Length: 15
Length: 18
Length: 109
Length: 107
Image 1 (tube, rainbow over the protein chains, first blue to last red):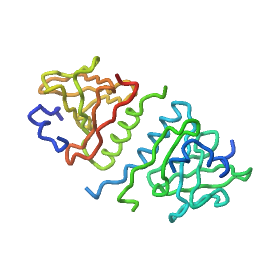
Image 2 (cartoon, chains in turn brown, yellow, purple, green):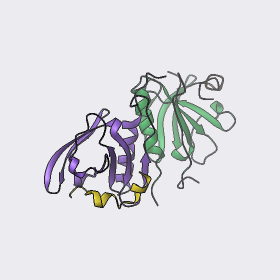
Image 3 (cartoon, rainbow over the protein chains, first blue to last red):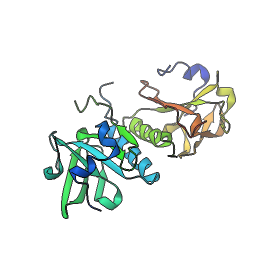
Image 4 (cartoon, rainbow over the protein chains, first blue to last red):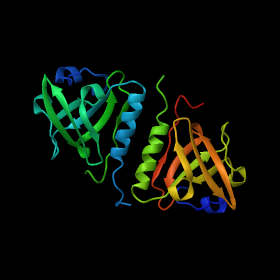
Protein backbone atom coordinates (compact mmCIF):
# COMPACT_ATOMS: atom_id res chain seq x y z
CA UNK A 1 0.00 0.00 0.00
CA UNK A 2 1.24 3.49 -0.91
CA UNK A 3 1.90 6.22 1.68
CA UNK A 4 -0.76 8.92 2.17
CA UNK A 5 -0.52 12.19 0.26
CA UNK A 6 -0.97 15.36 2.37
CA UNK A 7 -4.55 15.79 1.17
CA UNK A 8 -5.22 12.32 2.55
CA UNK A 9 -3.41 12.41 5.89
CA UNK A 10 -4.62 15.92 6.70
CA UNK A 11 -8.12 14.41 6.84
CA UNK A 12 -7.30 11.71 9.41
CA UNK A 13 -9.09 11.46 12.86
CA UNK A 14 -6.08 12.57 14.89
CA UNK A 15 -6.28 16.26 13.97
CA UNK B 1 17.88 -12.50 45.52
CA UNK B 2 14.99 -12.66 47.97
CA UNK B 3 11.76 -10.74 47.51
CA UNK B 4 11.47 -7.59 49.65
CA UNK B 5 9.71 -7.81 52.99
CA UNK B 6 7.01 -5.25 53.89
CA UNK B 7 9.30 -3.22 56.18
CA UNK B 8 11.67 -3.08 53.21
CA UNK B 9 9.42 -2.07 50.31
CA UNK B 10 7.65 0.48 52.52
CA UNK B 11 11.00 2.31 52.69
CA UNK B 12 11.41 2.41 48.91
CA UNK B 13 11.36 5.80 47.07
CA UNK B 14 8.16 5.03 45.18
CA UNK B 15 5.98 3.84 48.05
CA UNK B 16 5.10 7.44 48.89
CA UNK B 17 3.47 7.61 45.46
CA UNK B 18 1.31 4.65 46.45
CA UNK C 1 -14.05 2.50 20.82
CA UNK C 2 -14.91 0.42 23.90
CA UNK C 3 -13.94 -2.74 22.01
CA UNK C 4 -10.17 -2.16 22.03
CA UNK C 5 -8.12 -4.34 24.37
CA UNK C 6 -6.43 -2.73 27.36
CA UNK C 7 -3.06 -1.05 26.86
CA UNK C 8 -1.70 -1.91 30.33
CA UNK C 9 0.19 -5.13 29.45
CA UNK C 10 2.01 -3.33 26.65
CA UNK C 11 3.01 -0.41 28.85
CA UNK C 12 4.12 -2.84 31.57
CA UNK C 13 6.48 -4.70 29.23
CA UNK C 14 7.69 -1.35 27.83
CA UNK C 15 8.61 0.05 31.25
CA UNK C 16 10.07 -3.29 32.32
CA UNK C 17 12.41 -3.32 29.32
CA UNK C 18 13.24 0.38 29.71
CA UNK C 19 14.09 0.03 33.40
CA UNK C 20 16.29 -3.01 32.81
CA UNK C 21 18.06 -1.25 29.94
CA UNK C 22 18.91 1.55 32.38
CA UNK C 23 20.20 -1.17 34.73
CA UNK C 24 17.45 -0.50 37.27
CA UNK C 25 15.45 -3.02 39.33
CA UNK C 26 11.78 -3.08 38.27
CA UNK C 27 9.21 -3.61 41.02
CA UNK C 28 5.45 -4.07 40.66
CA UNK C 29 2.92 -2.57 43.05
CA UNK C 30 -0.04 -4.94 43.32
CA UNK C 31 -3.58 -4.76 44.72
CA UNK C 32 -4.02 -8.14 46.42
CA UNK C 33 -7.73 -7.44 46.97
CA UNK C 34 -8.80 -8.24 43.40
CA UNK C 35 -10.08 -11.65 42.21
CA UNK C 36 -7.47 -14.08 40.90
CA UNK C 37 -4.46 -12.63 42.72
CA UNK C 38 -2.12 -15.37 43.98
CA UNK C 39 0.67 -14.05 46.22
CA UNK C 40 2.09 -14.94 49.66
CA UNK C 41 -0.35 -12.88 51.73
CA UNK C 42 2.26 -13.03 54.49
CA UNK C 43 4.12 -10.38 52.48
CA UNK C 44 1.09 -8.22 51.77
CA UNK C 45 0.07 -5.24 53.94
CA UNK C 46 -3.18 -3.29 53.85
CA UNK C 47 -4.27 -5.01 50.64
CA UNK C 48 -1.05 -4.36 48.72
CA UNK C 49 2.26 -6.02 47.93
CA UNK C 50 5.44 -4.94 46.10
CA UNK C 51 7.20 -7.52 43.95
CA UNK C 52 10.73 -7.41 42.50
CA UNK C 53 10.48 -8.76 38.95
CA UNK C 54 14.11 -8.25 37.92
CA UNK C 55 15.73 -11.43 36.52
CA UNK C 56 17.82 -12.17 39.63
CA UNK C 57 14.71 -12.11 41.84
CA UNK C 58 12.39 -14.28 39.77
CA UNK C 59 12.20 -17.46 37.77
CA UNK C 60 10.01 -18.47 34.84
CA UNK C 61 8.75 -14.91 34.39
CA UNK C 62 5.91 -14.31 31.97
CA UNK C 63 4.55 -10.84 31.28
CA UNK C 64 1.42 -11.86 29.39
CA UNK C 65 -1.58 -9.73 28.46
CA UNK C 66 -3.93 -11.33 31.01
CA UNK C 67 -1.52 -11.81 33.92
CA UNK C 68 2.02 -11.69 35.27
CA UNK C 69 3.35 -15.03 36.50
CA UNK C 70 6.64 -16.11 38.02
CA UNK C 71 8.23 -18.06 40.87
CA UNK C 72 10.21 -16.28 43.59
CA UNK C 73 11.59 -16.79 47.08
CA UNK C 74 9.86 -15.17 50.05
CA UNK C 75 11.85 -15.56 53.24
CA UNK C 76 13.66 -18.52 51.73
CA UNK C 77 10.54 -20.38 50.63
CA UNK C 78 9.98 -20.59 46.83
CA UNK C 79 6.45 -19.70 45.78
CA UNK C 80 4.36 -19.40 42.62
CA UNK C 81 2.95 -15.92 41.95
CA UNK C 82 0.11 -15.08 39.56
CA UNK C 83 -1.35 -11.59 39.19
CA UNK C 84 -4.09 -10.45 36.80
CA UNK C 85 -3.15 -7.28 34.92
CA UNK C 86 -6.10 -5.54 36.55
CA UNK C 87 -4.30 -5.86 39.91
CA UNK C 88 -0.98 -4.40 38.71
CA UNK C 89 -1.14 -0.78 39.85
CA UNK C 90 2.30 0.45 38.84
CA UNK C 91 5.90 -0.39 37.99
CA UNK C 92 8.85 1.44 39.53
CA UNK C 93 12.63 1.10 39.86
CA UNK C 94 13.77 0.40 43.40
CA UNK C 95 16.82 2.64 43.11
CA UNK C 96 15.14 5.92 42.16
CA UNK C 97 11.41 5.45 41.75
CA UNK C 98 11.54 5.90 37.98
CA UNK C 99 8.46 4.33 36.41
CA UNK C 100 4.72 4.86 36.27
CA UNK C 101 1.34 4.38 37.90
CA UNK C 102 -0.86 2.84 35.19
CA UNK C 103 -3.87 4.72 33.80
CA UNK C 104 -7.30 3.33 34.70
CA UNK C 105 -8.81 0.89 32.18
CA UNK C 106 -12.48 0.49 31.34
CA UNK C 107 -11.83 -3.22 30.84
CA UNK C 108 -10.61 -3.57 34.44
CA UNK C 109 -13.23 -1.43 36.18
CA UNK D 1 20.90 10.33 33.06
CA UNK D 2 18.19 7.80 32.20
CA UNK D 3 17.63 7.02 28.52
CA UNK D 4 14.43 8.23 26.74
CA UNK D 5 11.22 6.24 27.25
CA UNK D 6 9.76 7.18 23.85
CA UNK D 7 11.10 4.30 21.75
CA UNK D 8 9.76 1.78 24.27
CA UNK D 9 6.37 3.48 24.35
CA UNK D 10 6.38 3.69 20.55
CA UNK D 11 6.92 -0.07 20.18
CA UNK D 12 4.26 -0.73 22.83
CA UNK D 13 1.56 1.34 21.11
CA UNK D 14 2.57 -0.05 17.72
CA UNK D 15 2.04 -3.61 19.00
CA UNK D 16 -1.18 -2.66 20.80
CA UNK D 17 -2.72 -1.03 17.72
CA UNK D 18 -1.82 -3.95 15.45
CA UNK D 19 -3.14 -6.43 18.01
CA UNK D 20 -6.49 -4.62 17.67
CA UNK D 21 -6.30 -4.82 13.87
CA UNK D 22 -5.79 -1.07 13.55
CA UNK D 23 -3.47 0.80 11.19
CA UNK D 24 -0.64 2.61 13.03
CA UNK D 25 0.50 5.94 11.63
CA UNK D 26 3.28 8.20 12.88
CA UNK D 27 3.16 11.98 13.03
CA UNK D 28 6.64 13.35 12.48
CA UNK D 29 8.24 16.79 12.91
CA UNK D 30 10.27 17.17 9.71
CA UNK D 31 12.37 20.05 11.07
CA UNK D 32 14.62 17.89 13.27
CA UNK D 33 18.15 17.25 11.99
CA UNK D 34 18.55 13.76 10.57
CA UNK D 35 14.96 13.35 9.38
CA UNK D 36 14.99 11.54 6.02
CA UNK D 37 11.55 11.60 4.41
CA UNK D 38 10.21 12.66 1.03
CA UNK D 39 9.67 16.34 1.81
CA UNK D 40 7.15 16.75 -1.05
CA UNK D 41 4.84 14.81 1.26
CA UNK D 42 5.40 17.07 4.26
CA UNK D 43 3.20 20.07 5.05
CA UNK D 44 3.67 22.85 7.60
CA UNK D 45 6.59 21.17 9.34
CA UNK D 46 5.10 17.69 9.60
CA UNK D 47 4.38 14.48 7.73
CA UNK D 48 2.24 11.42 8.47
CA UNK D 49 3.62 7.95 7.76
CA UNK D 50 1.72 4.67 7.54
CA UNK D 51 3.83 2.06 9.33
CA UNK D 52 1.39 -0.85 9.22
CA UNK D 53 2.89 -4.12 7.84
CA UNK D 54 0.98 -3.67 4.58
CA UNK D 55 2.59 -0.33 3.76
CA UNK D 56 6.17 -0.89 4.84
CA UNK D 57 9.14 -3.17 4.29
CA UNK D 58 12.04 -3.90 6.66
CA UNK D 59 10.50 -1.91 9.52
CA UNK D 60 12.84 -1.18 12.42
CA UNK D 61 11.52 0.53 15.53
CA UNK D 62 14.89 1.09 17.17
CA UNK D 63 15.80 3.32 20.09
CA UNK D 64 17.67 5.84 17.93
CA UNK D 65 15.38 5.96 14.91
CA UNK D 66 12.50 4.44 12.96
CA UNK D 67 13.62 3.02 9.62
CA UNK D 68 11.70 1.41 6.76
CA UNK D 69 11.13 1.25 3.01
CA UNK D 70 7.83 2.44 1.59
CA UNK D 71 6.19 3.53 -1.64
CA UNK D 72 5.38 7.20 -2.23
CA UNK D 73 3.43 7.63 -5.44
CA UNK D 74 5.04 5.29 -7.95
CA UNK D 75 8.45 5.34 -6.29
CA UNK D 76 10.03 3.13 -3.58
CA UNK D 77 11.76 5.30 -0.95
CA UNK D 78 13.81 4.61 2.17
CA UNK D 79 12.73 6.44 5.31
CA UNK D 80 14.69 7.27 8.45
CA UNK D 81 13.27 9.28 11.36
CA UNK D 82 15.15 10.13 14.56
CA UNK D 83 13.07 9.24 17.62
CA UNK D 84 13.31 12.87 18.69
CA UNK D 85 11.20 13.73 15.63
CA UNK D 86 8.37 11.28 16.37
CA UNK D 87 5.51 13.33 17.77
CA UNK D 88 2.81 10.69 18.02
CA UNK D 89 1.38 7.37 16.88
CA UNK D 90 -2.30 6.98 16.01
CA UNK D 91 -4.67 4.49 14.38
CA UNK D 92 -5.87 5.80 11.01
CA UNK D 93 -9.35 4.47 11.59
CA UNK D 94 -10.24 6.06 14.93
CA UNK D 95 -7.40 8.17 16.28
CA UNK D 96 -6.58 5.71 19.09
CA UNK D 97 -3.03 6.27 20.27
CA UNK D 98 -0.84 8.86 21.96
CA UNK D 99 1.12 12.07 21.54
CA UNK D 100 4.58 11.65 23.09
CA UNK D 101 5.69 13.99 25.85
CA UNK D 102 9.06 15.75 25.65
CA UNK D 103 12.12 14.25 27.33
CA UNK D 104 15.54 15.50 28.47
CA UNK D 105 17.59 13.52 25.94
CA UNK D 106 15.70 15.24 23.12
CA UNK D 107 16.82 18.83 22.52
